[PDB]
Image (cartoon, coloured by chain):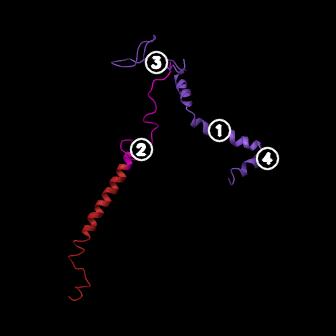
Amino acid sequence: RWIARTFFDGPEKNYERTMAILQIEAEKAELRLKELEVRRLMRARGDGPWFHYPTIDKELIDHSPKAT
Amino acid sequence: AERVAAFLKNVWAKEPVLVASFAIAGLAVILPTLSPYTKYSLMINXXXXXXXXXXXXXXXXXXXXXXXXXXXXXXXXXXX
């Protein structure tokens, strides 16, 4: 009982805790698997703003020339 | 003067062609900015049409008329 105080965390700790660490771990694992799933799609088809190659130009010239 | 009067007459005595290399080239840079005559040369340069003229379709527009002589458009008349 003396060893339980100021030397031990207790059974309440690491049961309420660790599950909190697992809750962050579950979020870290699912989003990393989602990142592997998103990059597998975004690289194959140019749909989103990920792995997009730069284009030539947006605007260059529109004025009237001396063309035929 | 310490070098204005001293290091000028020495340059005339020792290689005076070097005086011409700095003075004439110096006047080539300073004078174009000072003279109020460069504005006229830019006016005629833009006025000279190398390419064919283009007609714009007008729908309520000012400062534009027919191809005949009329008080419209730019048409530079700087010194005839």
**Whether residue B14 can be seen here:** no
Q: Which residues are magenta?
A: A39-68
Query: Most prominent secondary structure in the magenta stretch?
Result: loop
Quarter the C terminus of chain B occupies: top right
The numbered mark 2 sits on a residue in which chain? A
Identify which residue is drawn at 75% across, 47% down.
B9
The numbered mark 3 sits on a residue in which chain? B
The colour of chain B is purple
Q: CA distance from mark 2 to mark 1?
A: 55 Å
The colour of chain A is red
Front position among marks 4 and 1: 4
**Whether residue A65 can be seen here:** yes
Per the image, the residue denoted by label 4 is B13
Per the image, the residue denoted by label 1 is B27
Whole-percent x and y of residue A42? 38, 45
Amino acid type of the residue that numbered disc 2 sits on in the rendered structure: His
Per the image, the residue denoted by label 3 is B54
Circle 4/circle 1 CB separation < 8 Å: no
